[PDB]
Image (cartoon, rainbow over all chains, first blue to last red; front, side):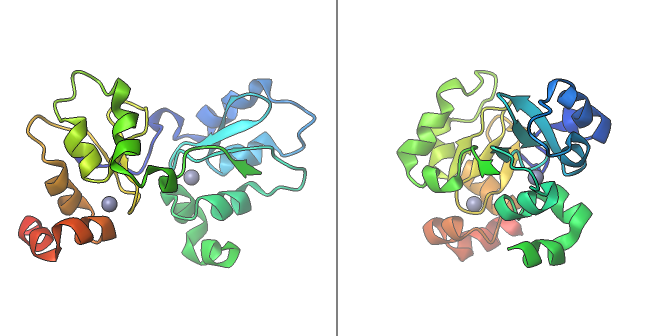
Length: 94
Length: 95
Ligand SMILES: [Zn+2]
Ligand SMILES: [Zn+2]
């Protein structure tokens, strides 16, 4: 067996993730560009997103929700979140 | 936002983990019995499994893979692994 850190290899790029928000509702008010930058792609319902790396799923996004802060709130061990924001950032949010 | 994906905390029992392997691919030649015993549950994607305790992810399972040995190979600090098999076993595998 091999260790893996990335659940969805097909969603590793920003463009691949951002494309999934083509049919995302304008009533949500969290920006799909920022969601995509934070590792998330749209998977169903009104606003379900998953992280391509940790495979964590978040929904019921509130206006003013910060995609990176939510990622660190719920999924602090995510290796993508660590690579971009660093463990200091995560420790701060936790 | 709210999490909706499954938590490692729901996978603490052998039975709950075993249950996840209902659709485990026939082509993957490692038995769900030994996987569940070793702390792993199936995440529904391909042959990806995760440990309920250390959250380690393993894929690409090969014929004859011993899940306990693989757990010790890749995640030697896992507290579940330590509790069941011991550090003597883990050290043995690591060298
Ligand atoms: Zn993540
Ligand atoms: Zn483990």
